[PDB]
Image (cartoon, grey):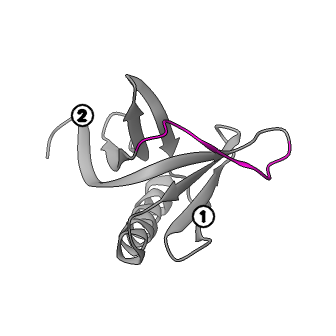
Amino acid sequence: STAREQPIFSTRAHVFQIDPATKRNWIPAGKHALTVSYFYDATRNVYRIISIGGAKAIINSTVTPNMTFTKTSQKFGQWADSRANTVYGLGFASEQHLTQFAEKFQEVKEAARLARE
């Protein structure tokens, strides 16, 4: 619990990102399903969504007080990251998995809100 980086939640999902030019077409990021997790950075007092693929951080989004995750199908969800200047999309294996990720997003945003004070 005293770790610099504390794992919070991990799940599997295929990752995508909206095309930066028109923000209409979805572009797969790392074709295969990857582990997507929420971590608590005790060094910066922030929560982050991280996903590693091909020795690269396909996702490293800091969860801010007004960042929102929206379900756009029964198994897909997305969120805009204004800091990173992109939009991430996740395709889960089931509706239950999407629900799990979304509920954790909300629980973690609450922390960020209090974290911001």
* Residue 113 in view (yes/no): yes
Residue occupied by mark 1 = 68
* Residue 61 as seen in the image, left or right of residue 94: right
Front of the two marks 1 and 2: 1
Query: Where 78 falls versus 26 (above or below)?
Result: below
* Residue 116 as seen in the image, left or right of residue 85: left
Residue 75 in the image: state x and y as whole percent.
Answer: 49, 70
**Mark 1 vs 2: CB contact within 8 A:** no
Kind of residue sitting beneath label 1: Thr
* Residue 96 as seen in the image, left or right of residue 58: left
Q: Which residues are magenta?
A: 22-32
| Inter-mark Cα distance, 1 to 2 | 26 Å
Residue ranking furthest to the left: 1
Quarter assignment of residue 32: top left
Of callouts 1 and 2, which one flags the residue occurring earlier in the amino acid sequence? Answer: 2
* Residue 40 as seen in the image, left or right of residue 61: left
Query: Where 107 falls versus 44 (above or below)?
Result: below
Quarter assignment of residue 103: bottom left
Q: Residue at x 36, y 69 (%)?
A: 97
Residue 86 in the image: state x and y as whole percent.
Answer: 68, 42
Residue 89 in the image: state x and y as whole percent.
Answer: 57, 54
Residue 28 among those drawn in magenta: yes
Residue occupied by mark 2 = 4
Quarter assignment of residue 66: bottom right
Kind of residue sitting beneath label 2: Arg
